[PDB]
Image (cartoon, helix red, strand yellow):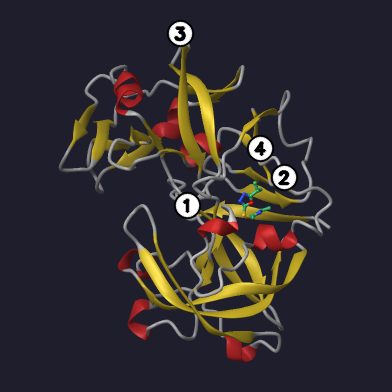
Amino acid sequence: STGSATTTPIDSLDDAYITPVQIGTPAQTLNLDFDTGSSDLWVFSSETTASEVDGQTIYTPSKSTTAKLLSGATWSISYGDGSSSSGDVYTDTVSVGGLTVTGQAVESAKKVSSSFTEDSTIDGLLGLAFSTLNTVSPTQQKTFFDNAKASLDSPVFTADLGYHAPGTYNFGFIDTTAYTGSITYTAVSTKQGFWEWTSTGYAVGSGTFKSTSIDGIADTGTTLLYLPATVVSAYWAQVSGAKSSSSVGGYVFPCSATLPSFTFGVGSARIVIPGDYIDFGPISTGSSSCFGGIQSSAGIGINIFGDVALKAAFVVFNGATTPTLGFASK
Ligand SMILES: CCNC(=O)CSc1nnc(C(C)C)o1
C-alpha cells in the first residue's frame, strides 16, 4: 500500500504545516501537524476542556462506530517549545492520503496548553519519530508509520515541504519526479528515539564550506533551524545590523536586509537554503526588526533541522532495520 497527502502552511510564514487525516467511521477529518520530532497522535476532542477549544475541529469518539476506549491508558506530553497536552486514548481507524491503519491509538486531549488553544488551525499532532518516544501509559503505543510499515510497498515516508506553498507527505514510495539530481542517504541513530543524523558542515552565502560534524534531528514539527552558536553567529555576521536580542528571544535583523543563503552538508552533497527562507518577518506588526530563521540551539541541548532546512529538500525517512535519512535538492 501507499498514501499521499498534501500538507499546507498554516500561515504566510510557514510556521507549521497541516495535513488532513481521516479518523473513525464515518470519517472525521482533522488537520494535523505531522511531527517527525515526536511519537504521539493526539487530537482535540469532545473530551477537551471546553475553555481550551477555540475554533479547532474536534474528534468525537462516540460518533465513530470503530472507536474503542483503550481502557486505563493515559498520555501526557511536553514539547521543546514549552507546550503540552494530555488525556486518554481510543483506538480507531486512521487514514492519511488513502493509506489506512486500523487499531491506531488516537490520543484524545482532555487538556491542552494555551499555545494549542490559540492556534485554531491545528487540530492535533501526528507523531512520526520512533514509537520508543510515545507517551501512552501503561502500554506504550505505536505511531501511524510504525503501524503502517509492514503494509507499505517500501518502509519509508517522505516529506516535501513547500516554501510559502503546499507540499506533500508520501508513505510507502519515493516519488522520483519530486526532486532533482540524486538522493544522498546518511546514517540515523534512534537511541534518543528521534530521527538523529550528522551533517557534514555548512557554508554561509557564497562562502567556503566548513567541514564539521553537526549532530541534529530532522524535525518537521519545529519551524526554525537551530544550530550551534558558532555556526549561527557566523551566519548572522553576514547580515548588516543583525544581532541577538535577549528580549525578543533570538537573532533579529533589519527587515530591509537581503539575507544570504545557508548551505548544509549531507555526506558529500549540499542542500542550499535560500536567504528568503530565513526571513520570519517583523517581530510584531509594523516593526522594522525581523525575526531570523536560523537560531542558536545552545539552550536546547540538541541541534534541530526544522522546517527552514527541511523545506529546502526532498527528505526520505527510511524506517528499515538500518533507519536512514535521504536528502535531495528539488
Ligand atoms: C518503522 C518505525 N519503527 C518504530 O517507530 C519502532 S521504534 C524504533 N526505534 N528504532 C527503530 C528501528 C527503525 C531502528 O525502531
Q: Residue 1's quadrant in the figure? A: bottom right
**Neighbour class for label 4 at 10 Å: few (<14), some, many (≥20)?**
many
168 is higher (above) or lower (below) than 295: below
Q: Earlier in the sequence, mark 1 or mark 2?
A: 1
The residue pinned by badge 1 equals: 16
Instruction: Report the side of 208 relative to 141 (left or right).
Output: left
**Neighbour class for label 1 at 10 Å: few (<14), some, many (≥20)?**
many
Q: Earlier in the sequence, mark 4 or mark 1?
A: 1
Can residue 252 be spotted in the picture? Answer: yes
Query: Please, what secondary structure does the residue beneath circle 1 have?
Result: loop
Query: Does the numbered disc 2 mark a residue whose Cβ is under 8 Å from ligand 1?
Result: yes
The residue pinned by badge 4 equals: 324
Residue 59 in the image: state x and y as whole percent.
56, 80
Q: Residue at x 58, y 59 (%)?
A: 131
Nearer to me, 193 or 17: 193
Amino acid type for the residue under numbered disc 4: Thr
Decide: marks 3, 1 in contact (CB < 8 A)? no
Q: CA distance from mark 1 to mark 2?
A: 30 Å
Number of numbered markers: 4
Q: Nearer the viewer, mark 4 or mark 1?
A: 4
Q: Nearer the viewer, mark 1 or mark 2?
A: 2
The residue pinned by badge 2 equals: 321
Q: CA distance from mark 3 to mark 1?
A: 31 Å
